[PDB]
Length: 162
Ligand SMILES: [Cl-]
Ligand SMILES: [Cl-]
Image 1: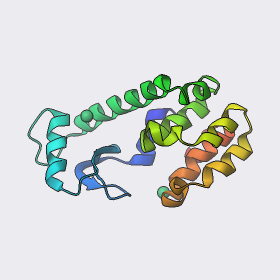
Image 2: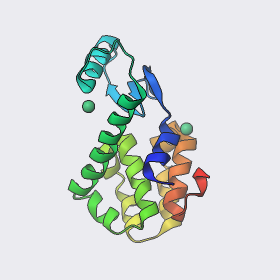
Image 3: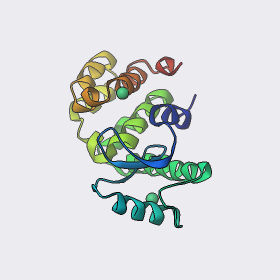
């Protein structure tokens, strides 16, 4: 199992614009198109992102192309971030995938804000980190996905995804 397969499980694949959990216009593999209520602003962004006139529909390849760009941006966002970087450098490869999942989902800023949890992740205090991570809107809004990511972080194994 790897970050890509982990995220494709968590986000699904949709070839047609849809709304996310939060209500935002999304497409492919968790690719947020806009937070604007307009489906027309969504089609615009979508067309921009893809380089073509899509009419709200994309091919599998296109969805994969977007996903590759997003995981990449996610990793680079982590390594460019003064709050995130140290935590990541300190982690083994499984737990790293966990932080990457979070950043893909909630943006760098979002995660960078989990101050306390990042600190316990750094100090390798797994259980406590797991408990603190659960005290978040994130966990309350998307409990099953969050529980999965959180267990990956606590344990350093891919069990929750098996
Ligand atoms: Cl884009
Ligand atoms: Cl969920």
